[PDB]
Image 1: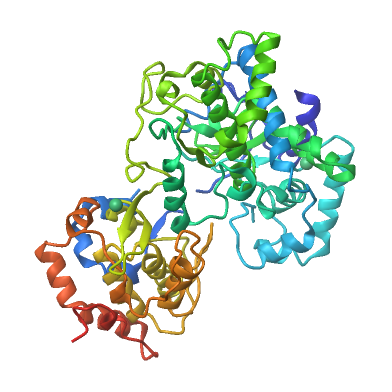
Image 2 (image 1 turned 120 degrees about the horizontal axis):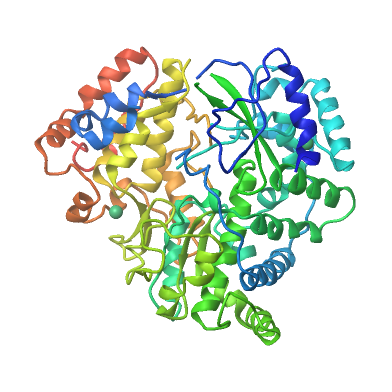
Length: 582
Ligand SMILES: [Zn+2]
Ligand SMILES: [Zn+2]
């Protein structure tokens, strides 16, 4: 407790010594509370006018229009300590899984130089604005790096002063850029060197991309076994136990020298003990602490979520196969049995899964998995929207399984080749493209964001009639040479000024390991759509009079947006579609 967090606490107490007060009507039950001090401030969602002017039929669809308007009582819940048998299962599995992940990878520190380049081309690193404005500035100033040095030497000394979380089913904990560096230096290798790639982790999909995920689910479907299970956890980050945080820390057993010590410090001082500043309107700042739950960078969060999810799902598979009888306690011969299962079939069982952070799909050996709930519930990974002891419902068709907020269609091209394409409710796709994050956006910047959505749609959602038409309209309305942008960035092949037909051919044909015939496609008309009824099922407006008038009059909408942006060089992409080709 207070010997590891006191220094951070003491330090904050003193920057607001004219403010401090141990408030009496404080709302925290499960968070240790330490004091308050004076502040007063809050970024809401703005509409992208370029995308909305080119999607007029959607102006009357509540599922689209409501997306642009607008539980912190789940962060304040407590998970019980797992039974001794559960803790044994987790430690054996975690030890074995880090060794597997480490067979073909070398832990290493990430560098200032690597970190600088990241900030100098925008990644959502989650820092705070003070002493310098943006992240960009602080990185070129040498003072910063002395701040970083003091903290670093403090961490080598087993102490911490400035690694404090700032709170804001979402809950995003920003730290100052310095603390993010020290996190990145110690643990960035997990992401930077692709430890959760499919090739390296067998269950993972890190760096895949939506054009790969459906082919991966279809490969899992090919395995002999039972239904496909895709159970979501209720508030995954809130159910991470101190025992989970300790099994994650075992990655330091593969490390050496300084690195081993820097990594141990991040795990001990920032993850297994945390200090957080929260805004309360009754507006003060509350300095609360706790030992458990997830609070890391979004990117280390992804890797450790994937790891701990892989662990939980191998254990649930062990329970379904009757590798152990009870979670109360493992016998000695049950430990040998668990160790032996892992060595004999562990890699085969990883390959039966697709795991992306807290999201999973499992194709178990058979349907006993559905009612194998004791380890899963005791680890605290309680399933969303189903009674705790009710058996899971599995999917009989891989095209119906939900994964990474998508389902996947099998689409046959006129030449017989097979596309496995990503899909979701079209209202969700249109509603997101109509939103910009942040203000101060110029017309040009708003246009370049609309173009990024348009190019993503041409590459991923070309099979949806409304999206191929709206993508062509947006790319016709935005100056041909203007570069697509995004303010927070898997593989993003649509972020380019290259011709989208050439990019389509590279992604879907040339680089696609599931396509044997590499004959290029010569026009967009070779590239198929979903069945018209399937397109409607997935939210198409095809068949409505509003949509017919939009399609027929699209050159008028394009010309409206061209007039607003002004006299620039434009391309007409609409004749890439049969119906505008004269
Ligand atoms: Zn620190
Ligand atoms: Zn669909």
